[PDB]
Length: 256
Image (cartoon, rainbow, N blue to C red):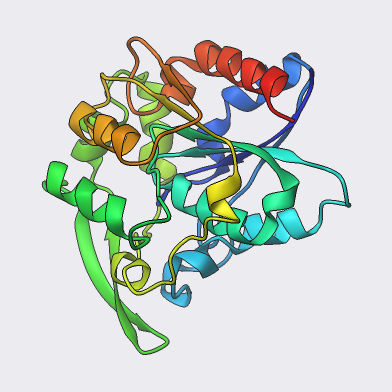
């Protein structure tokens, strides 16, 4: 079977992170959309214009609004992209065949939306040469960050080639987790986000989303299906591109 995959990058990143996986999925016959979220990739906004994870998610919500009735997609979110998935699913649950989490945060419906982010910061508190700044939007102080190049090299792109690490140095931009905004956001709903099928994909060799964190998430909110990829790094769409495409084909043949 063929599906329409919507690929959702993480904070400080853009559609470009999917530059290897998108053509591979298309060679299997799928339709693929790889979005730039707000103030990401070549989107023309700057992060200081964005006031929350929901506003950050606008291009995904606008895309889903534009799907004609009856068309469903499979969302694929990497790292922090899981939060964008939950926000989208509380607005467009009927257009989502399933959601795939790719070394990603897995929000739930019983705890506040910041819950798994707070836990991530406990498990991985030292972001190395990452820098931080503060800005104000809609009366709230938001912490912005710029991922540090050592952190990129050692922890996110550990086993990626130098030409891929180079793309990350060139193209990563200031962003935000909006942690304090999430912490005051209404909970993700059970009828919306809660109802979608969730597939959890991960590697135990991830040097930032460490096994203690990913196994904690799986126990906290049971996925419908779990796939463990052997080897690679946090950026499995670069280091295990073919394996990720194989998994996504199976998801396409399972959920519609």
